[PDB]
Image 1 (cartoon, rainbow over the protein chains, first blue to last red):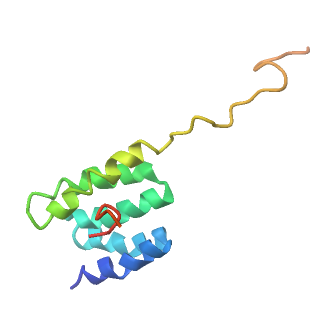
Image 2 (spheres, helix red, strand yellow):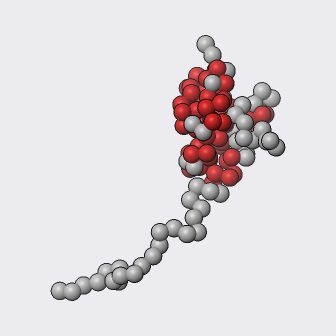
Image 3 (cartoon, chains in turn purple, yellow):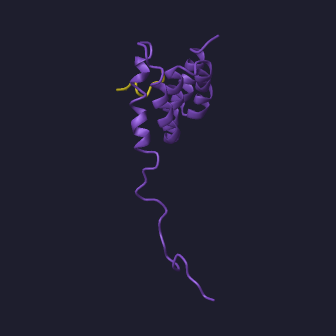
Length: 110
Length: 9
């Protein structure tokens, strides 16, 4: 059994840019220890760098279900960081595709 | 750097 390597191998894939490929090994941290925060913490930090903040917000608040111990205080600190920036970015767009240059929203001709 | 927030574990 292991957890560390699946957390140390993607530990550079995420830092390179391969965020999803990095999570693609992080996801086994949660499947091996679905009651462990760093599982969610690794997969979560990558979702910000992918901009799937929507999912990132879910990962961080999940980690806090397991931080009942001081081996997890490290991550309890993160489940509060990228938890906040994600939900403050998920859909934050003050310049979306909202333009009109043609007919009414419900014209008729017959 | 200035973070552990942008590190994994």
